[PDB]
Image 1: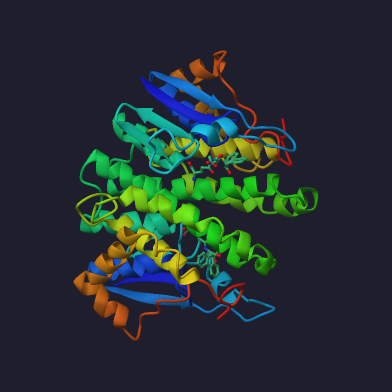
Image 2: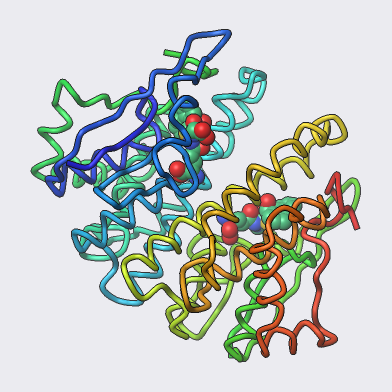
Length: 217
Length: 217
Ligand SMILES: N[C@@H](CCC(=O)N[C@@H](CS[C@@H]1c2ccccc2-c2ccccc2[C@H]1O)C(=O)NCC(=O)O)C(=O)O
Ligand SMILES: N[C@@H](CCC(=O)N[C@@H](CS[C@@H]1c2ccccc2-c2ccccc2[C@H]1O)C(=O)NCC(=O)O)C(=O)O
């Protein structure tokens, strides 16, 4: 089977595991335990970082035989092509490309913060920006069932992850956007997702580990 | 024709203009002003940011008829598909997907620094990592003429921008990687490239303007 390499948290892998499962992909996971604090030791990673034959060594990685991939987005695209979950029209391709890029921006923004020693201080002015963040996705999706269109695609995976993460962070963040809650429910409804999601293996959380300001566990 | 919206800067637009030209695109520009120190005023942008009918309001943007694309990479990709500047084989795509993601990471890395209040201190430390970064590009590239393979692709535009920029920051950063040095010369060679670059409407510098801790002009 393929090997998926990542740290011991939800993270950037949330959408990959969700993808793999959805597609019934055959895979094994390769969990990297990060040392504790202070340390936060990454030796277990660092010790093989350059020994896996990775183009630009990183976490997460997917090894599918001779095929060695880094860059979560890359990993995603790779699995999308494999299972045909890319946009089928230019329109769709564009929507997915914007979305893919957009999720990362927002993901990064949150991440940045939860790892900001000075959290508490900014943790409020930050929450000031979420409704706009959310409204963006809201207007975009509009009435479509899926982010690219009528057909589910890989970016739904990313979209799902991101929305869930904000929600989780700011529980009300979605009350104003019913379309967005419908989506969450619709993705959660995909038959292979519900089981997986109720699985012992499955760790809804936490995108973030020990190093975290909000959720250091 | 097509319209391109950006900040008086080079930044994210650099790869875009380069591709726009390469492909002989016919387009107009809508340049916006970034208020100064302090201020760093973007009224205009802000006065209209919400009036363009764009999906995720942002700079830059490219309007091509019905087509309104935000996110620089999406922009890049839309132009790539249009002129067949994408990877053609599965292998070419992976390389492309990887490099693209990799370039942005690296760009952000440098931008974050340039935008850090504690830049002077951070700098030396940041310098220390260059070789490694550079190294991965060099090896990933190996002996290929282009990042994805035998033919120029959009990622070449990404890569050149970024390599050109690290090279200005750390003029020696490349001495140990001649494939890289060739790549730069070779990229600058492309007929339509030299052509545009020689032109009077070409802006190399800088990636960052005002705010910029490094390259504030
Ligand atoms: N652009 C890349 C980013 C990859 C990334 O930065 N990887 C970090 C982990 S994600 C990173 C993180 C680190 C530790 C713990 C948690 C996280 C995490 C979780 C969720 C979201 C993002 C993060 C980042 O801090 C890493 O540890 N790489 C190993 C290395 O560089 O040698 C991608 O999308 O794959
Ligand atoms: N992920 C998006 C990034 C878009 C974005 O961050 N754009 C910023 C300007 S570029 C941005 C930047 C901002 C300030 C100063 C410098 C920079 C910069 C300079 C060079 C390269 C990249 C940047 C970005 O950090 C912006 O002003 N958007 C309009 C808005 O805010 O509504 C993309 O790739 O398109």
